[PDB]
Amino acid sequence: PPQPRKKRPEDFKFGKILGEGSFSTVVLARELATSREYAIKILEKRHIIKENKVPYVTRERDVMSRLDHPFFVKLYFTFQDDEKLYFGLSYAKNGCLLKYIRKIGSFDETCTRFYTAEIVSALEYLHGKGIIHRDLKPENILLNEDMHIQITDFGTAKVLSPSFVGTAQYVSPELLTEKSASKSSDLWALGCIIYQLVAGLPPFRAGNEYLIFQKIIKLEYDFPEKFFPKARDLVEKLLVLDATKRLGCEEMEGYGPLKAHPFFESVTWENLHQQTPPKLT
Ligand SMILES: *CCC(=O)NCCNc1cc(NCCS)ncn1
Image (tube, rainbow, N blue to C red):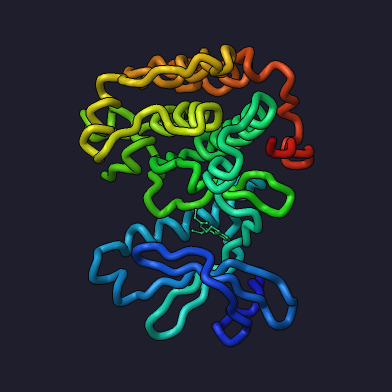
């Protein structure tokens, strides 16, 4: 099998900086021959080698190549010169989910339901292929032109075959105690997102990381008075201190029961990406 010609920087007309990470820079670029917009992640090798992020960059590449699903950002090509690596990723036109959370204050019942469903749909794929995100957050969940989700950031994800702490607010308690992450770590992260979509804020917030960590292990959060009752129950079955008792985990017998939850009564899981996402309040 012959892969398309190995690309090079000159093949593009670079545009605005979409995002700036710690080890990389993401710039919108247009391919010259095709006139296609790709978001090229640009990483400096010398800075990668010194910071020991060689595994992290490799893992990000390997995972995003393997994913073949609409709710996940596609890696179209990899190329490099002397000092830099270039990652040809898809361009999420609308931006962060967090962006749209802040913009509208909080999602209503239909909007939450729909976008919750898409994350579940995508998680079932990711965990089905034996990968654990470990850093799932509204910032990582991106939205394309038609306003569907496209989950990104897989450098820190864990691939299973038979050591890292994520963003403080969406961290599961078993990471802070046992140093061992599972599929259900993401399902904890899922519950926080469901809460955040309804409340407008994640469940655990404080002045610093330590106090946030403190509240998580103690399970210190509570619901507003208007919080959707069927969404509340789902969160309750997802934000559990014991990872084996979390709705959706292997001990809770896969994703079937999670999808079955009353909160997803009207949702047709058939073809969500072909469906039309609700407008945001
Ligand atoms: C929340 C911050 C933000 O807006 N980041 C830029 C996201 N836009 C974007 C991302 C990508 N790929 C993500 C690779 S890390 N492509 C196109 N636009």
